[PDB]
Image (cartoon, rainbow, N blue to C red; front, side):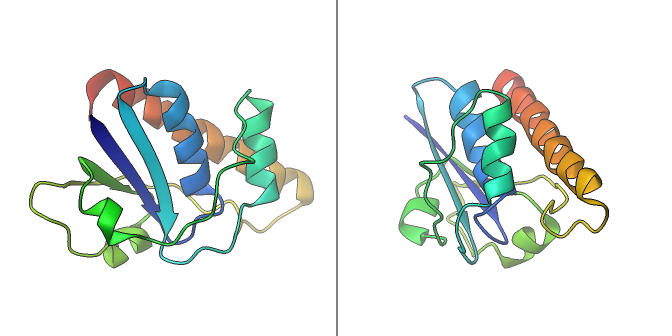
Length: 137
């Protein structure tokens, strides 16, 4: 009935966590997809971070953007400014929404700070999906 397509620079961290949160918050009415401009596989830290909150994204695949799917979506949600810049032209009926989350994989710091960063971005994405689930954004 409804299709939501998450897009980010890659399909390893943010986009995979968004897919996981969306499948939890949205009911059996929404088809959820996530992809990246490039796809280099699931980030282990992202998988662990989601597991910590009871969500298993270990079976999710790392996919490159597919216009056949994107063009049929009710809305595409870019997860950072770079993704917004690189998101291809879509049919006028597809809503283009832009959210923004820091890349936990590029964080510099102590190992404890970096792990905390993954957990923080995970929580920010979840709370944003909660807003979408309630308001339709």
